[PDB]
Amino acid sequence: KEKAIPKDQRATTPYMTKYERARILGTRALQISMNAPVFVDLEGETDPLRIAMKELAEKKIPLVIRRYLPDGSFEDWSVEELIVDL
Amino acid sequence: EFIPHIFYSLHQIRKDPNNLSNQLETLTGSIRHRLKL
Amino acid sequence: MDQENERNISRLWRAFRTVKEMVKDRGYFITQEEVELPLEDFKAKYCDSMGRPQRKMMSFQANPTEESISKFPDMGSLWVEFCDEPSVGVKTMKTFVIHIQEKNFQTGIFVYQNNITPSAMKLVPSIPPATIETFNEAALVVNITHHELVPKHIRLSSDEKRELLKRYRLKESQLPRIQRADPVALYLGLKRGEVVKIIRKSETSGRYASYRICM
Amino acid sequence: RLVKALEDIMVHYDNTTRNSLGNVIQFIYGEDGMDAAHIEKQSLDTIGGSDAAFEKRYRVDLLNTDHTLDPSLLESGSEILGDLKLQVLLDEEYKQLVKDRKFLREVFVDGEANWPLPVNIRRIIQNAQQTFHIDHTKPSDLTIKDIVLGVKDLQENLLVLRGKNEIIQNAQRDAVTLFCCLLRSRLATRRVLQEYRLTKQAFDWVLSNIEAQFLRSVVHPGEM
Amino acid sequence: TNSEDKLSKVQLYEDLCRYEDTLSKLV
């Protein structure tokens, strides 16, 4: 647990890349398509990808991204606190 | 200070309306500046 | 006054100025006036009645500035000596080595004209911690560092090296490297395991700083 | 042969560029850390031109009749004349522009002005003029203090590297040097008040849009 | 919140208000 960086000493970008966005959407779409509970008010949609986008819009995806520094340490960022461009 | 400046600009308005529209517009802008501040 | 005399005198004066520039660049104390000494004063001082260049009187001792001592506490005085013989014999090299050792100098510069016998250079690494470096005369006429394509290099202290290594979180075997025989490395006199910083121009950002290690 | 040679190079989260063994190839990708598709050709106006044209274009003086601001341009043009702090600020700005001219002529010895850079400032200013229906025939309500402080703060709010020790600070300033030079070139006080005639609302809009469009041009970690 | 209510209570506040309104009409 020595690798983990304290929250105050986080020196990575506070925006989320396109790769992280695509990975998160894919994971959430798979979990929804495997009958996982939905955290938002579904309105007439039957596609897991669109419901994943909808959950992302209200920032309700309960996932955490771990970013690997080259030496081996890592930095943990919640999906709620990552700024997503539109 | 805005009070004496408002007074003075008021008086050269009321003394010389025959000034070209440029001076009138600029001076009214000046009064708008003083009352904005 | 044959033309070869003044040709050799001018080339020797050029080499002297270049060596002074190098010693100044190594962190030592050299005045600007001494660097810009006109060739007339050089002829007046370092030539005999026949115009023969008296190289033996050009040997001099230099000391580091306050700033260099503050940045490098281990830095010490330097001595530079010229050799009159076309080829350096074993006895001359031994005499120079003994002179350096008895003066207790940490480093010395030995400029030779044409060639050095192998037995003479056998004694180069035999005096630790002193360092003996040789510079062929034909290669010091023109200052390399004054070219347009050569960026400006700086030497780094132990503290600065440690701080950079920590901040980028690296091990010294992953940085880009620079050899020993590299002309700028000889100019600056970099040893094994020393880090040199480079400042360069760039079409995209104006200025850019790189680093390298001497391997 | 080319693709096999270079196949294992990747931008990391340290913003460096390394390989599979961890050796650093570049300490910053491209020396400014910008994506290759967010870069357009823009001209640095400080390099070229004679000294007279430069002096006329960028110098403003509140004490000499030669280089004063026409009071019909600034709403508070009458009262500002003869002030002391304002001319000190303008002098600092002009010294900065002179140093920028010297540096830019040091870099590009050919004297060329068009280079690729991020953010098209001309289009942002044109959009500000088109959206707010700015009429050039009326005085503007801007303040010299506000213009200078706003430009300096916007420079303060451009970030590619987010370290905290001095090394990262130096690296980040070195990265953003040339863009700051262009930004100073386009947003000079005389240019704003006399060439664009922007108001306060349009000026705030331009600054916010410039910062937003810059922050979206950095390269995404993970790119091969 | 009561501060602005107290400020509106004194006449010279209304005075500056309609003075601003009159200059708005003039401009």
Image (spheres, grey):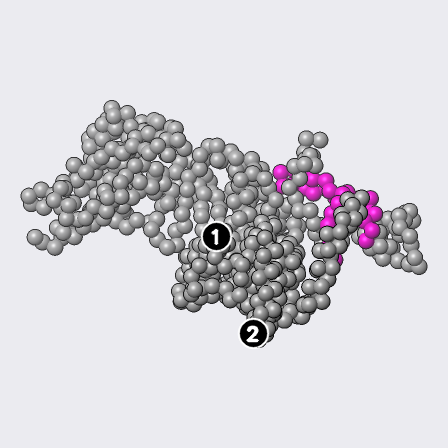
Where is A38 relative to C166, above or below?
Answer: below
Where is B27 relative to D35, above or below?
Answer: below
> Residue at point 53% right, 65% down?
D71
Q: Which residue is mark 1?
A: D84
Nearest the viewer among C197 and D154 is D154
Residue type at mark 1 is Leu
Task: Classify 10 Å Cα crowding around label 2: few (below 14), some (14-19), many (20 and above).
Answer: few
The answer to whether residue A75 is magenta is yes
Residue C111 x, y percent position in the rendering: 24, 40
Where is D152 relative to C47, above or below?
Answer: below
Mark drawn on residue B19:
2
Which image quadrant for residue A50? bottom right
Numbered range of the magenta stretch: A57-86
Residue D180 x, y percent position in the rendering: 53, 55
> Residue at point 50% right, 51% down?
D85
> Residue at point 13% right, 42% down?
C45
